[PDB]
Image (cartoon, rainbow over all chains, first blue to last red; front, side, top):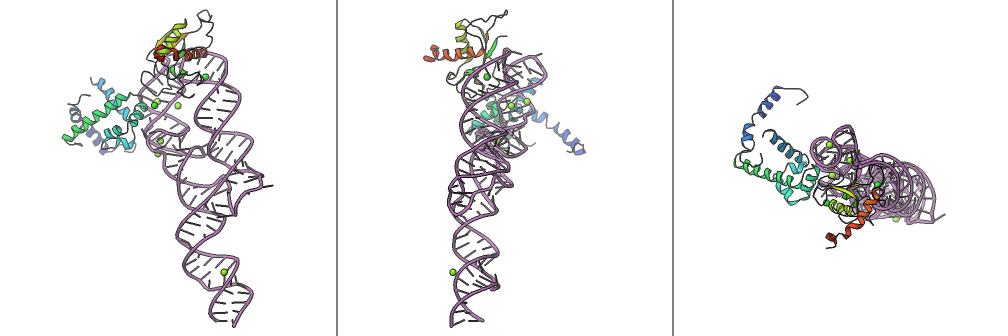
Amino acid sequence: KHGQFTLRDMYEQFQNIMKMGPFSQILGMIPGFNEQESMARLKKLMTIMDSMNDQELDSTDGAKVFSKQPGRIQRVARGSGVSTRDVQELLTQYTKFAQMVKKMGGIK
Amino acid sequence: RFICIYPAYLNNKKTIAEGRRIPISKAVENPTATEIQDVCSAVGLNVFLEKNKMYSREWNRDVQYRGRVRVQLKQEDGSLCLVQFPSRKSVMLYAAEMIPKLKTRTQ
RNA sequence: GACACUAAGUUCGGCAUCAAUAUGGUGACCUCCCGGGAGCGGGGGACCACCAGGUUGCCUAAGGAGGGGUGAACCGGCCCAGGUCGGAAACGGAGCAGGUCAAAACUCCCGUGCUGAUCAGUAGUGUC
Ligand SMILES: [Cl-]
Ligand SMILES: [Cl-]
Ligand SMILES: [Mg+2]
Ligand SMILES: [Mg+2]
Ligand SMILES: [Mg+2]
Ligand SMILES: [Mg+2]
Ligand SMILES: [Mg+2]
């Protein structure tokens, strides 16, 4: 996009609003999902990642990265003013979410 | 109007920039806001513990590492509460010296 | 004419490149105060590392304060979104991610010293 607006843009936006209900109902069987009281939980989880680096983000097995090198968890916790447990929690949900995605597809 | 005493102030494991306020020679291992309050209250000082407050220069979030302690120096009229305690430095030091004596530490 | 010797030319490689100083910086750490209800505001000393361009030792066959790079998950310095902490607030602090760099560290390429080999066969001199 270029500070402007093309039909593809309008398209992609409508498209985002699509992979909603789905992705939303995919959060179905995952203890860690009250609309407003959820947004926070979702914004938190994001801010925590706002502290991870590319290599950590783009890792097929993020859980392990952090597993194997705990210092990374500490770096992240402290870097996002959140607790350590919080980070490990975010890490497990990401796992559950991964495993889930596996049983189905991924992009959708 | 009471004053502020953060454990970082009395921590010999912290550098200057990390919040240490007294010479390492007088500083202490890992003073806990609790211990600080427990020695101050036991000298005739008026003080209350702010259990959950956290020192800004304290990256850690654990418990042994947080809390704040508040002591009354002067009295509304102006007179110091305890002649032997002018400044804040005075209290910090007095605390740094008495904690390594708390039974809970000599244990 | 053919060979030699000194000066010397081309190219691809190898080995190797101080010390101690002033002034100004940046950073780190320590140590004293004043002010303040916090985050802090203010001021004096000490030590170490590094940088900018500036000397000199009486220093080596050489040793220029040259030009890049990388900067690591964190573990160098800066700027630090968000979030976090102190704060009623204003703000301030610690600080990851991200960006960045006269000044943690580590590395190249320059130059400069010897140095194999290569190519040229010019400059002089000498011999038969
Ligand atoms: Cl001070
Ligand atoms: Cl630590
Ligand atoms: Mg010869
Ligand atoms: Mg980088
Ligand atoms: Mg880094
Ligand atoms: Mg912020
Ligand atoms: Mg800061």
